[PDB]
Image (tube, grey):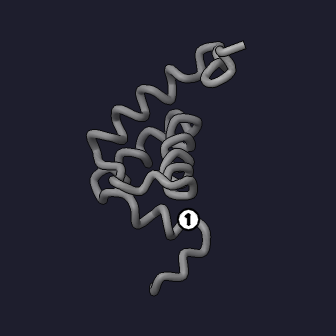
Amino acid sequence: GENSAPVGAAIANFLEPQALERLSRVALVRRDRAQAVETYLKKLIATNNVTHKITEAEIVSILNGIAKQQNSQNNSKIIFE
């Protein structure tokens, strides 16, 4: 209750009921994917990105990217030298 936000409560309220259930199902098979979804939300809110939440449409799209992200790659901002 209240606006305490221990650690995961702050991000738990930034999700959808239907989307939350989906994340639980995927985590059962691939926890790595579900871990990135929960960590991604906290990353955006903790950083500054707080203009939208994660719905069933967003969670499915991000989940697909999460699995694809782990495909032997580590270049994002270090490609200018």
Judge whether 68 appears above or below 17 on screen. Answer: above
Q: What residue occupies the far bottom of the structure in this picture?
A: 2
Please state which of residues 39 and 75 is positioned toward the viewer in this rendering: 75
Q: Residue 32 in the image: x percent, y percent?
A: 58, 36
> Regarding mark 1 in the picture, which secondary structure is present there?
loop
Q: In this image, 76 relative to 41: left or right? A: right
Q: How many marks?
A: 1
- Residue found at x 56% / y 53%: 47
Assess disc 1: are there few (<14), some (14-19) or many (≥20) residues with their C-alpha within 10 Å of its C-alpha.
few
Judge whether 76 appears above or below 48 on screen. Answer: above
Q: Is residue 47 visible?
A: yes
Q: Residue 25 in the image: x percent, y percent?
A: 41, 43
Q: In this image, 12 relative to 69: left or right? A: left
Q: In this image, 60 relative to 4: left or right? A: left
Q: Residue 45 in the image: x percent, y percent?
A: 50, 57
- Residue found at x 52% / y 45%: 40
Q: What residue occupies the far right of the structure in this picture?
A: 81
Judge whether 54 appears above or below 33 on screen. Answer: below
Q: Is residue 21 visible?
A: no
Q: Residue 48 in the image: x percent, y percent?
A: 50, 55
Task: Point out the image quarter for the N terminus.
Answer: bottom left
Please state which of residues 69 and 33 is positioned toward the viewer in this rendering: 69
Please state which of residues 63 and 31 is positioned toward the viewer in this rendering: 63
Task: Point out the image quarter for the C terminus.
Answer: top right
- Residue found at x 37% / y 57%: 15
Which residue is the site of mark 1? 8
Residue type at tag 1: Gly
